[PDB]
Image (cartoon, rainbow over all chains, first blue to last red; front, side, top):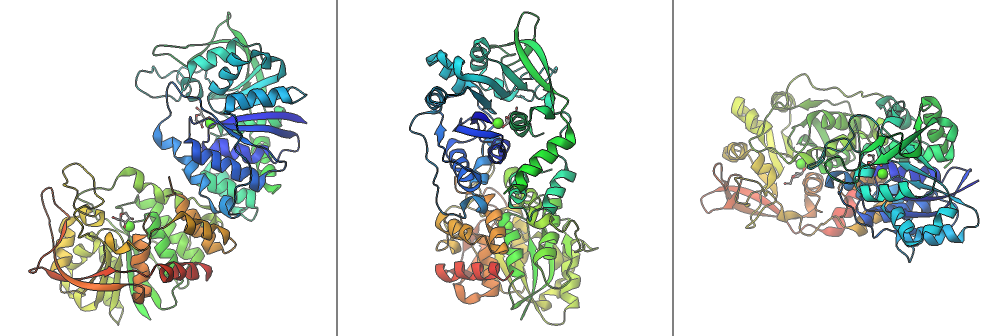
Length: 300
Length: 302
Ligand SMILES: [Ca+2]
Ligand SMILES: [Ca+2]
């Protein structure tokens, strides 16, 4: 049983991952928080609360970030939570029961970590700024962090950031706040990294969307399919979440690394023999991965 | 029983309209066709075919337009069909049975109208260019048109078109092809207009979305809700109201006004009331409760 604190930024994948983490027997979410990076805050807060009401177990709260980004995501990607938050499945109950936490995400994270006895695993599928902030303000939290699992970075020649001022070598979660990645990388914590590359072997395919639609009878599968209709014809965050729940889906190669913090290469992650250790996921088992998440969806 | 030929441009409310027409006991769809105006053609074609498969009755075909627009819709509005087409409810069967018609939409329209013995009601919820074109090639078709019900136009000082080269006075279905509107306007046909204003009394509201979500148990209500999630609160059901007026004329009133359309320059697509113009029957004073009760009744029939 792993105690997990989950900070996400409200894309379809972040929200799908919330849904799946809640079906893992092996995981207990101590807290959820939302950062307005790849989302607008209000729909992502709401959708998270409704998913926990609908598909959750214990009583938990969702905290809102008041972090601000250096390099904001494209407005069009950010809209997706409005759609998820509007799905009938998530509105059928006509009530939102799970509470917004009183404290902002970074303070919520601090308070949750320090109030849990056991060390907790941090799962971040958006930028790292709520964590950089928690560290800056209360670095004793190092002692409560088992490890950080983060969707971010790439060690290919080019990333997924194609934006003015940028050289095109960074990945989005890092580019959104390179200074936060730097701070996290100075902290004394173990870091498992799901990079852009890490997901090579599990592309979300039309044959996989169509197999899901065939099993729409399962309400969790129907829900998965409504979520991915919004981004129609890689599951970065889902893979990250799934690696927390089932480490054996993939392998990990320890590399030494730095993050660039300014100029046209800001956000870029670079392997250096001088840098700090980072355990980079590779070699995802296709069949096991997709069998795992459809198993989990069917538990509802 | 009304014979209806339906031309739509594959926005969310076009596709929702198709689904609801199909539940109306007093309507028999003789033909459906898709124009790539507020949609990309492929997802709109597929979505229409899958809707007819899952929720339709008799065997019909969907024709693809090869009409082109003068003033294209914004890209981001046009994507919405991709999402509806990808919804699991519509992909559960794993096959698409209803056929694409062999002819393009304007030709399809002509052949359908002339092959059906009684007159047919034309229902257009996108631009008018498949009809303009039908009329240009085969004006005999006036003889088979009971009337046109069209979502288009506005008689307010401003419309919903906010685009370069335009003065902001037109509505989108007219603006997409103003020449087509002019051609239809010159035809000897009766025209019922659902304008932008027509819908004032029936905003889609959060309270209505939520009340639909509560009855998700009905698969057609759940389907309606999925469709409207795509266009969520951050809205007026213009096309759905147009389609409902065909099924239940008694939901609204109509005022006959004489009208022209501007065809060129910064005011292109503008509809203007003139004592000299041609008669158009403009919908107003929609009964809120009956309208929304009607479409929720229709959704529950599946
Ligand atoms: Ca994310
Ligand atoms: Ca339309």
